[PDB]
Image (spheres, helix red, strand yellow):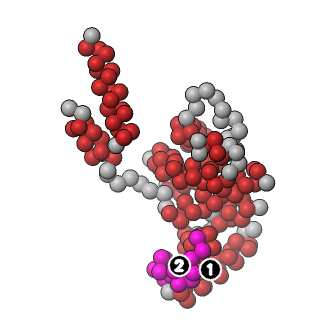
Amino acid sequence: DLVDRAQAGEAEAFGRLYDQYSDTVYRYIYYRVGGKATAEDLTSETFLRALRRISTFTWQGRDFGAWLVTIARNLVADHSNAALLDAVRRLNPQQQECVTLRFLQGLSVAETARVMGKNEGAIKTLQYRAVRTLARLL
Amino acid sequence: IANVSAHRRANAFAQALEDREQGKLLALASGLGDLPKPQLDPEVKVVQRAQLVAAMEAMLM
């Protein structure tokens, strides 16, 4: 390889690497920082660093999971779409979840309401306030 | 002599764990592994994964 496939710029292969390794990276980080949000942010940063250096990941005895762990270790020690998406990460919990479910997952207002434990009216209000906030800080 | 045998059982256990006297050891490792672990928020995973796939497409565009 999945790694070898990502090194071919198959973007979805790198998505699959995230699927396979994200929880392990998160768990390594979780117990070493103050707060879930920080642990989530450094998990994202760990993968982003691996991705940006993936063209160098070619040394003899390399191991991708071990590399991720060593990168996260370094980060904890040192502790357009990209702009669109990092804007999303800045929304408060409710607004972030609303935009993620509605637009990143493609759930309807009704489906989103069921997941969030809110009424569809509250979802229509929430998605409006969420996109308006993206419009300001972006 | 008995030093190389301790090495062999260790290697057998390692190989067994990947797959999963020695059956008790595996049961203990499974017992520890079966406990609930902290999990990345599902909705956070959605956004992070999308950020990474996009960063890749940006690298290759």
In this view, the residue in front, B14 or A53, is B14
Q: Write down the region rendered in magenta.
A: A105-118
* Horizontal and vertical percent position of residue A58: 66, 32
Q: Residue furthest right?
A: B61
Asked whether the residues under the numbered discs 1 and 2 touch, taking CB atoms below 8 Å apart as contact, a structural biologist would say yes
Q: Amino acid at mark 1?
A: Gln
* Horizontal and vertical percent position of residue A70: 55, 37
Mark 2, chain letter? A
The residue indicated by pointer 1 is A127
Q: Amino acid at mark 2?
A: Thr
Identify the disc placed on residue A75. Answer: none
- Image vertical order of residue A3 relative to residue A95, above or below: above
The residue indicated by pointer 2 is A112
Q: Residues within 10 Å of mark 1 (few under 14, many from 20)?
A: many
Of the 4 image quadrants, the one containing the C terminus of chain A is bottom right
Mark 1, chain letter? A
Q: Is A6 positioned to the left or the right of A21 in the image?
A: right
In this view, the residue in front, A93 or A114, is A114
In this view, the residue in front, A99 or B5, is B5
- Point 69% across, 35% down: residue: A56
Q: Residues within 10 Å of mark 2 (few under 14, many from 20)?
A: many
